[PDB]
Image (cartoon, rainbow, N blue to C red):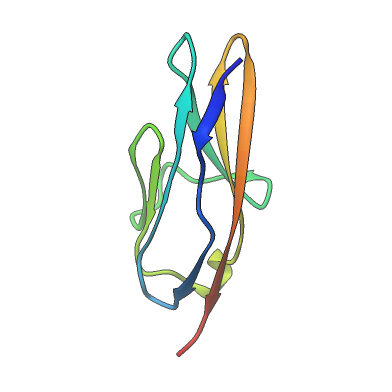
Amino acid sequence: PPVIRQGPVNQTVAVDGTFVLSCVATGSPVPTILWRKDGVLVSTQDSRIKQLENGVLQIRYAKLGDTGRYTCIASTPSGEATWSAYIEVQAG
């Protein structure tokens, strides 16, 4: 089964700022990382949301609606692992 060693860390983000959510997973085969925001897979087609590397998710110019829980999903045919962090976004 895939094992998540370092998971996303909770953070307070200001509106229009930039936040990064990283994730490190171990296993044979090499686990694939997927991101879920409030039970819905993070879009691969948003100009501001970039899935940099397998395990790193960057969100530039943060909206108020970006508030929620982000889940890091490590996938291989031998199982699946999850790690969650809540990201809150308030105005100035």
